[PDB]
Image (cartoon, rainbow, N blue to C red):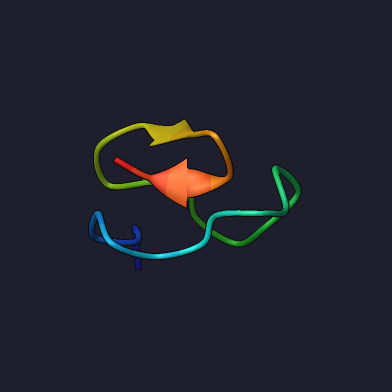
Length: 28
């Protein structure tokens, strides 16, 4: 369920981290 870049990753305690790397509250 990793999030593909272009999304707002704002919840380190989420189900899945950024498929890539979440930076600046933005899946990069």
